[PDB]
Image (cartoon, coloured by chain):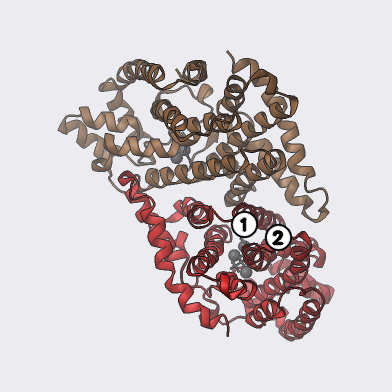
Chain colours: A red, B brown
Amino acid sequence: DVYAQEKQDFVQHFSQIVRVLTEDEMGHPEIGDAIARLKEVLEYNAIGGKYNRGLTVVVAFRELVEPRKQDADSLQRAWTVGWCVELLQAFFLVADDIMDSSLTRRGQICWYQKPGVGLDAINDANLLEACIYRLLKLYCREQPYYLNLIELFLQSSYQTEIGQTLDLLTAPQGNVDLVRFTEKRYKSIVKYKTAFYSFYLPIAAAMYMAGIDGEKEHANAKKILLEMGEFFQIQDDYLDLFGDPSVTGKIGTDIQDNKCSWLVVQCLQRATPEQYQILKENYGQKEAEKVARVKALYEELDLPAVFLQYEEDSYSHIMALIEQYAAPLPPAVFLGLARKIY
Amino acid sequence: DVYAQEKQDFVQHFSQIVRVLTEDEMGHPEIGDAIARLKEVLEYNAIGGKYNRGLTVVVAFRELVEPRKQDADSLQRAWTVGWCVELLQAFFLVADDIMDSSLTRRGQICWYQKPGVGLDAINDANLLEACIYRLLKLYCREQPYYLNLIELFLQSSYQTEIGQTLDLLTAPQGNVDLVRFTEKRYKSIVKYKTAFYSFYLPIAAAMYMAGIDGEKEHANAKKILLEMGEFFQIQDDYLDLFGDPSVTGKIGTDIQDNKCSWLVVQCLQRATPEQYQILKENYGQKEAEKVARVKALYEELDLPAVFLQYEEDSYSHIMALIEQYAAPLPPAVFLGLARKIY
Ligand SMILES: CCCCCN(C)CCC(O)(P(=O)(O)O)P(=O)(O)O
Ligand SMILES: CCCCCN(C)CCC(O)(P(=O)(O)O)P(=O)(O)O
Ligand SMILES: [Zn+2]
Ligand SMILES: [Zn+2]
Ligand SMILES: [Zn+2]
Ligand SMILES: [Zn+2]
Ligand SMILES: [Zn+2]
Ligand SMILES: [Zn+2]
């Protein structure tokens, strides 16, 4: 709701993001072709998603900053930082799609799968990352929270990349990796690869912009936000297999990629030795029939109903955490986020 | 000389770099496997080079900072920042080797070509980049030049990535791209992809650490250092084809990769229409015989003698620039660098 009534404005501001990321270099004609390639990268890879992470910066900013301090310049900085979180996401997704050998993203073919792009996409991804710090300098250099924001984005990237490392290490291609797929391992992976940048980062950014920099307030916010992030990634795992492709915008690869997904972890906890064997001989391979066998096993073990029940229990757990840890922040900050993902 | 007598110490300090980049996370057991993977990444990809860029930080620091201010802690910060430049290099090289489809680097098989690594190397590369800002925070957070260093590394990365973008855009695979290969295009590519991070960055870092932050002193240093960087990349292009593989540590790919190298640019300037045609039908392709035909054409046009002459003329030009622009810095700062690359 509050996201919906910030959204269209948020998106309209992308043109200014792209203009400033192109004009700040108009003094250097020789890099014109690169700046043009950057524009094409931005428009293909930063547009077409739900923009939830960026909108969260904007929404939380409005709720944390006194209305009389919400001048036009402060608002502009708010939705610039929001777009920075979107650019970080864009960076991650371009690189992750190569590494997961994915086909489609946000309803179109993955950037790297586009003819003429290929592994040049690696440099495109790093360029998207670079844009973050260009925008922070351009818009936030003279603000008291400047360094707090730089370090938050840098730290969030490190954490996410540690998470990606765990994701990859736990899913070696061509191996049978079932004994590695535990609940304890899973919770660690998603905490790092998803939870910090998708939930802590956006709220923390708005917090620092509102002058809320205390270690205690950030630790309490984090308690709520990392648990939301854990649920969100479990949801991502569920939809990878059981989601509507016209809604998700992308084709799942978790089974073919031998991933430690919530689904396989739950499967393992429930499987008979006979089902375990079936899982063992069909998981982590590219053959459609082997993947289909896995999905059949998940359905036989009623993992969809297990998920639906987990979703409700998680929601209740998250709301309990908000009762405990939200103060002194407006509870609406976390409630609006929860409403978005549940 | 001054590099040689700083070197072994510089290298010995790598163990402390690796220890601190592993222990700063010992409070988080769950990411142990990732930290182990990080260690393996560091040891494979940050070791085995000449360390010229890192040593330059250390050497320039000793020459710019008054001896009485060179305490043990300041020295330690100096060779930490030196290793940061080495980590940036490591980041770039891992990614560049994937994008150039290279086989060997520093005398061993490229990281991504190592069995079991593959495109996971993309995340490894970004992890190396992340380590830079972890070390700066760990060692330099309370220093007055902290933000200057963060912004210098971030800006240098952006510039290098713009350069990489130009490098890639000018070398589309499967196309004949000769008309794109001009001197003007070439100078732009190497200014951005090589010159800023390999020469300006290390000296600028030492400068900020010495308290030299004036725009004018940095602009004058840059005048010398970007020209050195241009020569250095021309040298890199020459050695890609004409260097001794047991000395370079790597196999060239510029011709197969259809690159705008100094060599092809010089070839084009000198070729008859008949030689142009030969270049056109053999450049940018993977067949050994076609590559060999190109190298034969270069040798027929005596590009090796052209290079040797250019190297001498460039040296003289660089020394002239040092006479003009070195003050108020010790000329030895730039002379030691020049001696390293010429
Ligand atoms: C490069 C860092 C990637 C961080 C991974 N994120 C969770 C987003 C990518 C995914 O969620 P996605 O389902 O591919 O969108 P994955 O399930 O592969 O983790
Ligand atoms: C990812 C950014 C790469 C920057 C490129 N640098 C010049 C180092 C790589 C090279 O010098 P290298 O010869 O492969 O070591 P390239 O000739 O491909 O440019
Ligand atoms: Zn993915
Ligand atoms: Zn992934
Ligand atoms: Zn997923
Ligand atoms: Zn290369
Ligand atoms: Zn290259
Ligand atoms: Zn080269």
Give percent across and percent down for residue B17. Answer: 72, 35
Q: Residue furthest front?
A: A68
Residue at 53% of width from left, 40% of height from top? B152
For label 1, the SS is loop
Q: How many labels does the image show?
A: 2
For label 2, the SS is loop
Of all chains, the one bearing label 2 is A
N-term mark: 1 or 2: 1
Q: Which image quadrant for residue B9?
A: top right
Q: Residue furthest left?
A: B273
Residue at 46% of width from left, 59% of height from top? A112
Q: In which quarter of the image is ligand 3?
A: bottom right
Residue under label 2: A213
Q: How far apart are marks 1 and 2 (CA)?
A: 9 Å
Determine whether, in the image, residue B169 is placed left or right of residue B115: left
Residue at 65% of width from left, 48% of height from top? B116
Quadrant of the snapshot with the C terminus of chain A: bottom right
Determine whether, in the image, residue A183 is placed left or right of residue B224: right
Say if mark 1 contacts mark 2, CB within 8 Å.
yes
